[PDB]
Image (cartoon, rainbow over all chains, first blue to last red; front, side):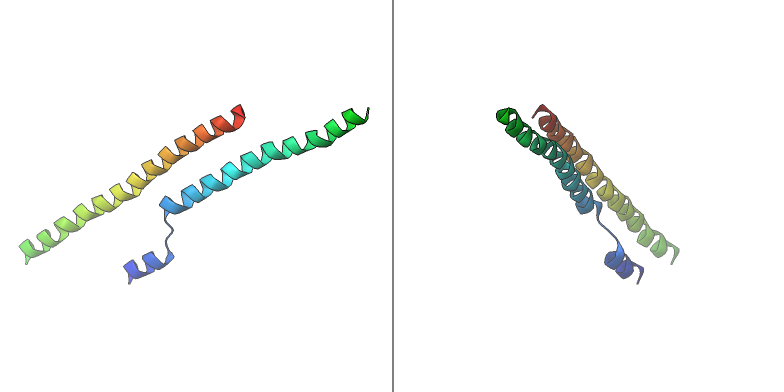
Length: 49
Length: 47
């Protein structure tokens, strides 16, 4: 019963850790890209000038 | 019965060692993909 409980309940790092990887990678890429978007209307303004 | 019990527990402890070695083989897989992810961060800040 302990084995059955363990297999139903336990989490596998060999999956969750790479899930964390993908997620945080996306977080950092998202931060950089978000920074990028602000420059666009700044260019718009410089053009307006 | 003593001989039987000892023999039965021997392989059990050995496969416990094997299971922990599995958890830590995958731990090293995760550190290796984390190194790959640090290299990804490398490309990302080079951007």
